[PDB]
Image (cartoon, rainbow, N blue to C red):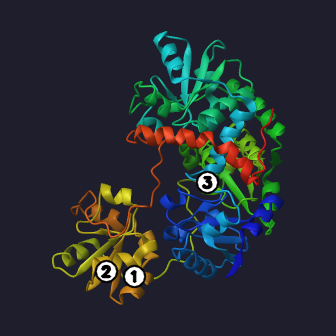
Amino acid sequence: IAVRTFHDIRAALLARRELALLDVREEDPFAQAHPLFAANLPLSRLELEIHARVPRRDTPITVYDDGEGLAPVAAQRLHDLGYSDVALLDGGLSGWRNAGGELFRDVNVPSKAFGELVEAERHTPSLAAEEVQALLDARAEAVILDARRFDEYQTMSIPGGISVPGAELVLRVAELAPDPRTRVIVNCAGRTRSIIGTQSLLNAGIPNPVAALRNGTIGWTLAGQQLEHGQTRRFGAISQDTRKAAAQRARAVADRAGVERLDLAGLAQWQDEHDRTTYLLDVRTPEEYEAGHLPGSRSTPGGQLVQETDHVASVRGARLVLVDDDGVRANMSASWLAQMGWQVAVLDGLSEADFSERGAWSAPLPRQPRADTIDPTTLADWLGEPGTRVLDFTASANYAKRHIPGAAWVLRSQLKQALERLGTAERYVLTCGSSLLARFAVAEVQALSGKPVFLLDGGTSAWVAAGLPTEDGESLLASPRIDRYRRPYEGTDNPREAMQGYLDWEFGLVEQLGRDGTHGFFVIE
Ligand SMILES: O=S([O-])[O-]
């Protein structure tokens, strides 16, 4: 395990050499401060995502934390998983700060900062919440398209809004706003996806007057206006005429942004070059993906690939190949990734036969460690007497929703502390949604406790499937709930102060990008 400094990372970013800068702390602390291109991969779930986010075993990986002692453990596990070029960031987070490195809060910062850059450079049109409300009061001919995931749209939405995820905008707009006089308004929860969506439509050159709802659902609430909930308005299937026209416009945008082209043979060649990381991504809807997709491809709906790029393409400097079956979605998404400095190509010449693999994406995993298992009914019997400690590794949010009675929620990254707090037990039984994450924790629990440790066969899902009783709420938390950053732009229970604070934070991103100076972003037109 070597050591790499802020300067080593900065040099690689400027030269655009592949690298993976991983913050191994939990998400909440990550969200308080981290380098622009640092990807968050909590030590707690390192093994579950590393092979997908950093596929090249010899990729220069640099892990860090802020002194918790998580980094050295992460480095060792990576070595044992087969990664040959692992290092610790000199001084950790503080080392980066002390060297003069720029630090950012929140999540998916490159994507959000880029969004602000687009508006700053192209002056992307926007309408105040009050102006849009007036249009509604005037029964104006206008459609409001929500560019977020369908589940976000269902949580809360702008009155009359229609769900049209980011990458679907250029493809579906002609069917939702056929009259060129019809105004098209794009919204999200905050600003990012609304800016990208509005500019996507302008870049594609639609005849309709377009504008982003300024500050989205957050702005709607701050304006004292009313949101709807549980809505189901959504885009529909389009005609071939609509598709062909939009595809021509999209391809032009992609060519303009420098998006590369590839055919199946070209793809195979890239995957044959072991000196580069190549992510094969399907930008269509989840439903289409599961109905049939290219072998080796991962499902990353376009709008979200552009919004949460670091969750998938964690190796900055890597190569991306996008898949779609319409000629619009991949081209548009690629144009944005190109502007965010990514080397990206769109896969051409695909036929219906190429989408042969079916079902949900199966993430690549390392060898599964061995463990002695116990059936749900046996565990129930054990719990009839004291002495059995059940540890739940699922996300704290999931735990609060439903868990095995008496189970203690824990952070895999803080097991020593959790076990001390819980006292002693005659035996431990580990669980999680399916038992997958808990299985990777067996060895550590055995080491720290020196007690018999078992894995619940099938996890909590199996327990529930057995008809056994469950308990909800924060029954017993043996670790602090820092596994998830409370995004001010998700849900409707965030205080107005936090929501306005989120907008203020985005307002300062372009200035921060200037101070960082390693992004290489550019905005076409
Ligand atoms: O992309 S929006 O929800 O901030």
> Is tag 3's residue or tag 2's residue first in the polypeptide sequence?
3
**Cβ–Cβ under 8 Å for marks 3 and 2:** no
Packing grade of label 2 (10 A; few <14, some 14-19, many >=20) is many
From the top left corner, tell me how far across and down residue 246 is, in percent. 72, 28
Image quadrant containing the N terminus: bottom right
In the depicted structure, whether residue 396 falls above or below residue 147: below
Check disc 3 and report the residue beneath it. 104
From the top left corner, tell me how far across and down residue 315 is, in percent. 69, 61
Check disc 2 and report the residue beneath it. 428
Name the mark on residue 445: 1
**Cβ–Cβ under 8 Å for marks 1 and 3:** no
Quarter holding residue 229: top left
From the top left corner, tell me how far across and down residue 83 is, in percent. 67, 77
Q: What residue type is labelled 2?
A: Tyr
Decide which of 11, 329 is in the foreground and name it: 11
In the depicted structure, whether residue 224 falls above or below residue 463: above
Secondary structure beneath disc 3? loop
Secondary structure beneath disc 1? helix
Q: Which residue is drawn at 83% across and 37% down?
A: 256
Q: How far apart are marks 2 and 1 (CA)?
A: 8 Å
Q: Which amino acid does label 1 sit on?
A: Val
**Cβ–Cβ under 8 Å for marks 2 and 1:** yes
